[PDB]
Length: 53
RNA sequence: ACGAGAACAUGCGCGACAUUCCGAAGAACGCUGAAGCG
Image (cartoon, rainbow, N blue to C red; front, top):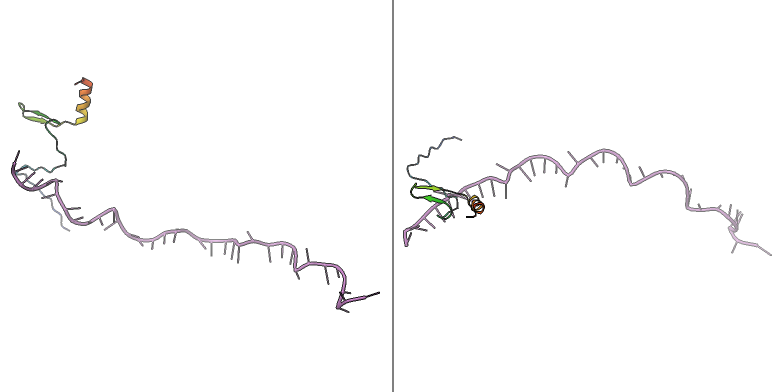
């Protein structure tokens, strides 16, 4: 059995899904900075509970 | 005034000794998190 090393050169963006979709409520979108902060829900909820927010 | 009268078919003695229910054996074969775009 022969073996080879596959080199996938990405000429177009590739999205292998994970079965999980989030909405703009779940994560952060700084439009002016144009950056999306992916956050985890439990930490945000506990932070808001600590801050009373 | 019975071929009769007594007279335990009895005594000591382990169904016991040696033994692997093991030997061989892939829970794996195929399987794009993807299709349409409203």
